[PDB]
Image (spheres, coloured by chain):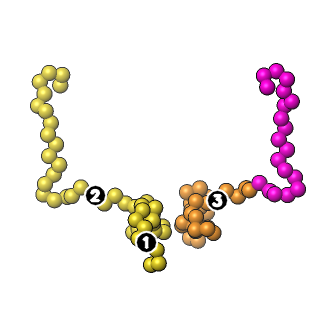
Chain colours: A orange, B yellow
């Protein structure tokens, strides 16, 4: 509190955190959903070199 | 206790440990001593291409 506000990425620093599942690498947030919409892979209807 | 003794390097596993100095990489044990003996660097007494 007795300093200027130091804004550095090497200032914002925490200890090691334990996530659910006892992993310590921070898990990737995204997981592809299982809703009514699937992954609409477009595929070229190919004539030459099939 | 109700298992066979499982001896694997992936069995011997601990959590994250905090060392003195608030480091978490396990520090190297060796530090060269400051006794009465210094590091006796041998150096070739060189004649050609000095």
Task: In this rendered view, identify the residue nearer to me: A17 or B6.
Answer: B6
Q: Residue furthest right?
A: A36
Where residue B11 sits, quadrant-wise, is bottom left
Marks 3/2: CA distance? 36 Å
Q: Please report the residue visible at 56 percent of the width from the left and 63 percent of the height from the top.
A: A24
Question: In this rendering, would A45 be left or right of B24?
Answer: right
Occupied quadrant, residue A50: top right
Q: Chain of mark 3?
A: A
10 Å crowding of disc 3: few (<14), some (14-19), many (20+): few
Where is residue B41 drawn, in percent x and y?
A: 16, 43
- Residue B30: mark: 2
In front: mark 1 or mark 2?
A: 1
- Give, as a single range, the part of the protein colored magenta: A32-50
Quickly name the residue at label 3: A27
Q: Are marks 3 and 2 on the same chain?
A: no
The prevailing secondary structure element of the residues shown in magenta is loop
């Amino acid at each position: 509190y007795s300093r200027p506000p130091n804004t550095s990425t090497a200032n914002q620093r925490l200890k090691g955190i334990i996530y659910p599942g006892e992993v310590t690498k921070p898990p990737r947030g995204w997981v592809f959903p299982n809703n009514g919409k699937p992954l609409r892979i477009g595929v070229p209807n190919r004539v030459s070199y099939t």
